[PDB]
Structures are given as C-alpha cells and as structure tokens.
Image 1 (cartoon, rainbow over the protein chains, first blue to last red):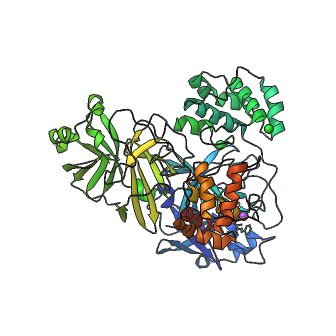
Image 2 (spheres, protein in one colour):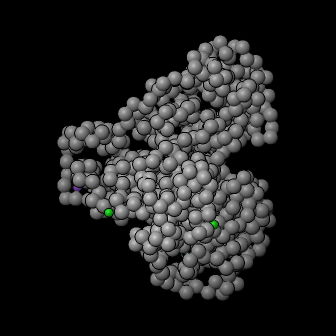
Image 3 (cartoon, rainbow over the protein chains, first blue to last red):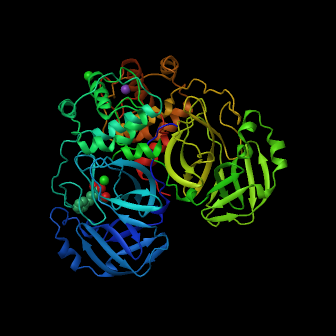
Length: 300
Length: 305
Ligand SMILES: CC(=O)N[C@H](CCc1ccccc1)C(=O)O
Ligand SMILES: [Cl-]
Ligand SMILES: [Cl-]
Ligand code: NA
C-alpha cells in the first residue's frame, strides 16, 4: 500500500530528446521516427517576440539554419514545415529509440508526467494535471521549452503536452503534439493571463476514495447530497461543477469501497466547511486534485 | 519557475530491471554486468518466511531453480550466492544496457528516486526520503519487491535502496544493494514496527528556500536565532537537531536568497509555534521535509544528466 504522486518511467521519452538551435535560441525537440517536433517560437528573434509572422520567418529559413543535436551526433535536417504552433524538422535518420507512440489531446483534469529537459538532456520527471483554466503548474526554467508531457499505458507512449511558455502568475502554457494550444493562449509575448483556476472536483473525490482504500475513514459522514445541491456548495469554494459523467467515472471506486458517489460528495461538502482540524489525508493537510479516478485504480 | 516533487530520469535503471522467479515467488531483479541482484526472500515459501534459514534454503537450490526473464529473453543463471539479505545470480550474459553505476549507502534525511516495478516491468517513478526511523513512505503493491532506489550524479547511477517488505503501518523497509537493512528490520514474517519518526529539519529549511526562490515570502520575518535556541524548539516539536554541517550545506541557498540560515530558522520557529494561519507554502499546508538542499539547488538551476 501507501499513496504517492507517481510519474511514468521516463526512459522511452529520454531516448527521444534532442537540442534544436535556430539563431542564438536553443530549446528541446522530440525526435520520433524521422521528425523532430519543437515549439515554432525557436525561429523568433528579440524584436519578433510580440507579433511574429511565423509563415514569413519560416520561409526565410533553409534546412541548414536548424542545428539539431542528439547527444554528440549532429542530425541532418532535410525538411521543415509548421503545423499550428509546432515546427516539424524532417531529418535523414529515424530515431532508433522511437517507442510505440501516439499523440492525444487531453481535457482539463487529466494528469500526465513531464520530462523537464535543458539543452536536449533530462533534468527530472514529475506529475502534472491540466488545470481547468488550461494551464499546468510545472517546474520549468529558461531553456525548458519543447519539454513534453506524456502517459504510458501498456508500452505505448501517449504524448499530450509540449511546453511553450510561462505566464506572469508563474504557471505554464503549451500545446498538444499537433501544435494546438491548450486554452486561449498564443505563442506571442503579448500580455496574457490564465482564467481563475478551480479545484478539479472529480479528482478530489477519487483521492478521498484512495484514502478509504488505504484505511482512512475519519472524514466520512452519514449524509448524502443531491448532485445539484453539491454543485451549489462546491462552487462557493471555487470547485469545478461535478457532472453525471464524473459520477459515472467514480462508479468502480464507489463499488470497491461500498461508499456511493453522492455519500462521498457529502463528505467533501463537510471537509470544505470544517477543514482537517490538524489531521492529514494520505500525508496532505489540503484536498489533493492531481490524481484522476484512473490514477487511483492503477496505484491501489 | 514552479516547484515539484521531481524524480531523477529513470531510463538508465529501466534497462536493468528483470523478473526473478524461484518456485511460486516472482519479484524484481537488478541486472548489472553479469549479476542479477534481488531480495534473498525470493527462495522462501510462506512456511519458510515465519523463521527462515536462508543458508539452508539456498544450498538446496540449483542455478536452474532461478528463472530470470529480461523482457521476453530467458537469462541462464551460472552461479548463486548470498550477501547479507541480497541474492546475487551470476548469468552467462553481461547487461548491454549496464549504465555507469556504483552501490552507495545513504543516511536518514537523504532523498532518492524509486522505480516501482511489477514482474520485472517498470510501472512508476517517485521521489522519497529515507525517514529518520529508516522507513520510506512508498507506494508498493504485491510484486514490487526488488524495486530499487537511486540517485544520478552526471552520468553515474548511485543505487542506494532495494525494496524487501511492507510494515503494518503502510511504510516500507529494505536494504542497500549490499543487502544491509536500513533500520532495525529483518526479512522474516514477524511483528515489526517503525520507530516513532521525526521531521528532517535541514530539508524543511531547504524547502522554505525553494518557496522564497519562487516568490512565496509571507513567512519571512525580521528575527534571527541561535542553533542552541532553535534546537530547544526543534526537540520540543519532534524535529531533528540542526547541526553546523546542516547550516553549511544551506550556505548556497542563504547566499542566493539573502536569508541567512538562522534568519530562516526564526521563520521555522514561528511556523512551528503559530502554524500557517490558513496560508500555504508552495501549495502545501504542511511543512515539507522530502527536499534536500541539493534537491532545491538542482531543481532551481536546471542540472541535467
Ligand atoms: C528562454 C525561454 O524558455 N522563454 C520562454 C518564452 C519564449 C517565447 C517566445 C516567443 C513567443 C512565446 C514565448 C518561457 O519559458 O517563458
Ligand atoms: Cl483526457
Ligand atoms: Cl473554514
Ligand atoms: Na527571520
């Protein structure tokens, strides 16, 4: 037993990380088969940060303006194109370490691992969630752009995130591996701000079910709630509305513990009213929202 | 910016994980050069685990009693020996993915990454501290025995931990890679309990420095203190004593933030005596003690492997 923030093993992603240089700008690229994916803003100069014309900056590049390095090996760029906010550099070598992979666009509430990289080398791995405001609370320094987020279900790597920028509140914005931004953000240094963030209600409930599976019962109560009454209370605490989809998704955890989803909702209403009274749940004195129903069933 | 519980990249270790089976027991092995390391308790039945005679159980077994599987490849065992509570299975093939590595023994308070594995297959990686009572607060299910803990320094993997068992409190016990237990534990089915734990003071301070580097500053104050004064408050709150060595190790973070260690100790004294008054530090309502000073320097400067 025990309950930990756990990331996927990073090895299958490590063997895909390269350094991409264009101008004086170096960041990370993802090398799959014969394509290197990286943030298109690698082609921006210091005066092209506010309103870059990516189509114009790209057409002025030759393949040999792109320096791609896989460890000590210079890769030969033989093609360049742009898909949304992702630059794709065709190279003359397929990565021999390419894992089985796919590209998946995730929804808010979903979790994934991030392999934080600098100069094409891995620094560390951690778990993140896509926040309801379409940001992630990452750990990223200058040089981290092109680091990716991923899940590994059953030997196949699902790439879901590529890191593009830090917003003024210190949270992170990026794209799927088709180059489409999560949320209303753009790859320009024009003033942008995340929407008000909310707590991921379904994930809190999943983590309360995990606490019960690990033998915590102190926060349970004898009450139930309607789905509608729960949402009226929870939104006063900046909690996301719980949908009938979310209720359904919790069904297996409901069945394993024999606590109905709306009984557990009453427990969460009460925890929001009382706080923890100097107690902890699974080692936290806050209600944790970065574990999904799927994460809890995998780990428990 | 941002600050997360961050593991080392696990790829160098993923290439060393194998499945070891002896009779009805399957758990994980570490394949380095031509030796597979695993818990010696792989040779035990249920009966055996109550009062095992490992010497006796092992001399009975032959090489062919150990089934070692590296993905879909059987390795041939050509030798078996025991070192303390670890079994060494010599195999006929050196691991071609053996990284630069050494075996190291860590101290309580030091952190490392665990690669959680099942049937020889890597499942998850997480960061954890060797607790002052020599347990780790792990996440392990049936079949995670032989999962390992490590640090990376440049291109060298330092292996520091092998998982052997769960204690009745849900915390975990194991050995270094030379088979020496961390803490007062034995590999038998018996009544064993974790000693009462204590907070790793130098790590809480490191984490307060991480918070300041990330602009979380409300807990800072005009006051300073002394080791002796702080250590009387520490002892009272079940905190490890702060040594001069610990002050020295925080040197870099004190320099890089403009908060002296004893200035930050005065912040920590006020937090222990007063609580957080409904506030949070780096998204926690508790004082976090599983980041070392080196963890904070590494994460906040982007050290790479
Ligand atoms: C050095 C670096 O990594 N800078 C990025 C923003 C760099 C950028 C440039 C052009 C358009 C959008 C974003 C960050 O992490 O904040
Ligand atoms: Cl999703
Ligand atoms: Cl309250
Ligand atoms: Na102070």
